Image (cartoon, helix red, strand yellow):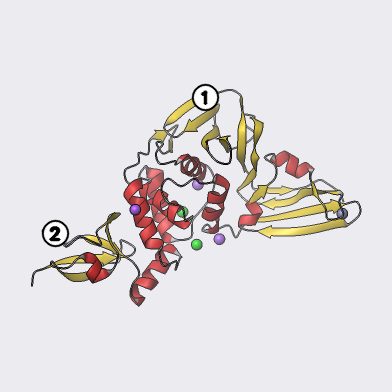
Amino acid sequence: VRTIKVFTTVDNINLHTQVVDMSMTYGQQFGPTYLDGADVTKIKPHNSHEGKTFYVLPNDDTLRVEAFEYYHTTDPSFLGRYMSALNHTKKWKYPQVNGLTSIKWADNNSYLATALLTLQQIELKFNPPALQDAYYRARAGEAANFCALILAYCNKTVGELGDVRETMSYLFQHANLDSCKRVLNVVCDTCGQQQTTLKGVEAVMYMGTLSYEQFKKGVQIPCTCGRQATKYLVQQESPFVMMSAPPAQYELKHGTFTCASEYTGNYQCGHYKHITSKETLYCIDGALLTKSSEYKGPITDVFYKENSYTTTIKP
Ligand SMILES: [Cl-]
Ligand SMILES: [Cl-]
Ligand code: NA
Ligand code: NA
Ligand code: NA
Ligand SMILES: [Zn+2]
């Protein structure tokens, strides 16, 4: 009966000694098993595996606690989805473009590239240690684990089409936004005024206009009575805001925004690019970079800096 020693893990930090029988597969001994992303479930131990670390599913109470503390999920398939994505993302390339970690286009990943570029330009801290650790590496240029985690947390597989606004929502759900507050007022000439207070992720996201200045002036929305109501920003406390809308031709003016996402094509199929406002307007499309003094395109999301805002509007 021949054996080697290997280590299992769910978090790649806490290791669990195992003595494995070389006549059985990893799967017969551990359940689904992965070696830096590669599925070894149906493989029998090799001598070269001695001393190496394998990921497994959180198959006992110790691992369940370790996995929840590191990832902040109890979705049973999470670890397998992360590993499956990592086996791909470890082969992607992450060029530094204008000082930021981007992603060379592969596997329909333009939505991930513009999300990653965006994160590097807004003040945001993640809650799960897994995203903390992986995001630090991604800033340094080694973004594979971070991208595989985005995919897993968003329930997206490599190659699946994704929406930037939705992806950001998931990332924000795993971020500490508890200092963010938004007060809105909605005014119907028939139905009167309704103030609402939004906290956390809802305090920093709005769907319906790209213009923060228009959101402060008031945007027209439906009311139940059939009139239009006017929605405006009363008060904002956050380090950024994200304004989104269905893609439409829109002019991005240098110095008036932080960065934006552009979507060319239609709902079936298109492509994202990233625009960042620095000393000029830079358009980052994966590995590609172009510049211009002005920019007009089908924009979907625009990010703005903020600290504290209070309206002058008297009601
Ligand atoms: Cl972080
Ligand atoms: Cl979280
Ligand atoms: Na896979
Ligand atoms: Na950031
Ligand atoms: Na949160
Ligand atoms: Zn009304």
Q: Secondary structure at mark 1?
A: strand
Which residue is rendered at x = 83% and y = 46% of the image?
Answer: 313
Amino acid bearing label 2: His
Name the N-terminal-most of marks 2 and 1.
2
The quadrant holding residue 43 is: bottom left
Residue reaching furthest to the top? 293
Q: Which residue is mark 2?
A: 46
Q: Position of residue 132 (x, y in %)?
A: 43, 55
| Residue occupying the point 58% across, 57% down | 177
**How busy is the neighbourhood of tag 1: few (under 14 within 10 Å), some, or many (20 plus)?**
few
Q: Is residue 16 visible?
A: no
Q: Where residue 190 appears, x then y in whole percent?
A: 91, 54
Q: Secondary structure at mark 2?
A: loop
Side (left or right) of 250 relative to 48? right
Q: Which percent across, then down, holds residue 278? A: 54, 31
Query: Which residue in the protein does label 1 denote?
Result: 291
Q: Which residue is at the far front?
A: 268
Which amino acid is tagged 1?
Lys
Label 2 vs label 1, nearer the camera: 2
The residue at the point 35 percent across, 51 percent down is 86
Do the residues bearing badges 2 and 1 touch, measured as CB atoms within 8 Å?
no
Q: Residue furthest right?
A: 190
